[PDB]
Structures are given as C-alpha cells and as structure tokens.
Image 1 (cartoon, one colour):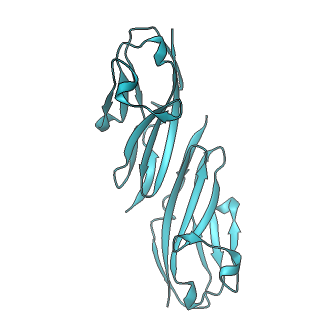
Image 2 (cartoon, one colour; image 1 turned 180 degrees about the vertical axis):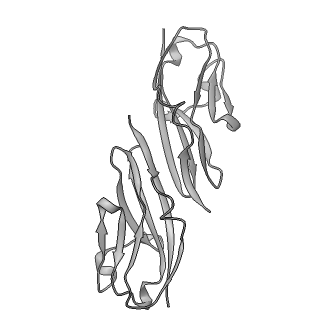
Image 3 (cartoon, chains in turn yellow, red; image 1 turned 90 degrees about the horizontal axis):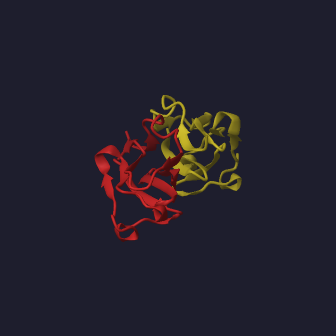
Length: 100
Length: 100
C-alpha cells in the first residue's frame, strides 16, 4: 500500500495570499496523507525556517499539518512553503504573508 | 492555481506485481494531474530506462501516462517506476514485472 504524499484537503490551501494586521496570529496548514507517514518542513523565502529566525519563534503542530506564528511583525512578511515528503515523493505549496 | 503532481486514478495503480508470459505486451500507467502539466519519466531498477535498453525499445504515450513494452522477454523482468514532476513536486510509483 505504499504511496507518495498527497494533499488531503485542498480547501484549506486555496487562500495563498494573506494580509494580516501586525500582532495577530497566523496559522498555515498543508493537510497531507501518504504511506509511510510523510514528514513536513517549512521554508521562508526558499530557505529553511528555523526557531531562531523570529523572536517569537514558531509552533509546528504535526497532527494538524500547521505552522503557527503568534504576534506577527513586519519582518515576518514573506513566502512560506510547506515541504511534505516520504521515500515515494516530495511535494510543496507556498503561501504569501503580508503584514498590514 | 499552481499545484504539485498527484495521481488521478489510483485504481489503475493498485496492481503492483505483474507476472506475464514471454512474448506478451505489458502496459504500465501512472495517471497524473498537476499545474503546470507534469512531465513523466520511467526508471527500470532505479536507473533511467532508455530505448536502447531492450531490443524492442519502448513506447511512451504521454496522453495516457503509460509505458508500453511489446513482446516481453525474460531480461525485461524488474522494477519499473514512473517519476512524475513539476516545480511543485516529484512523486513516484513502482511496478514489478515478472516474465513467466
């Protein structure tokens, strides 16, 4: 039953550009399936996004396939991409964050 | 509307192991979708499978996402994998061919 990653709910993913006021919380999701369970990682502007990249750091909820950034600030604007992978494939989606 | 490759009809793909008498024709398919249109390539035992690898050569029908090998011979046994890709992702599936 092995199978490459696939998005399980594209509805959540249709809204690509997000404009949010500073200090609000943004949450990005890339619901996925696959056998074996794929892993997920996030890039910000094409480069690995790490905890130390912003003051507030960030939360990853694997069960919900989401990236959460609390109290956004202007320097958080950018492109956020979820890369999901397993031995049979690697797929990605990109969101754009604009901080109003 | 950009989107990574995805299989559009997994039904065709459920039968992974194929045992076929010599001299018969085998056809493998990996129906796929994605935006932009993904490309497809085939590997035989993990390595690029080229026309010169077998006497009969092989047919690729892009419209139907299939690899066709006429008059199979014992040396054709092996693992056949369709790799489908576009800028948003790369996915693969593997079939096993046994020549009876």
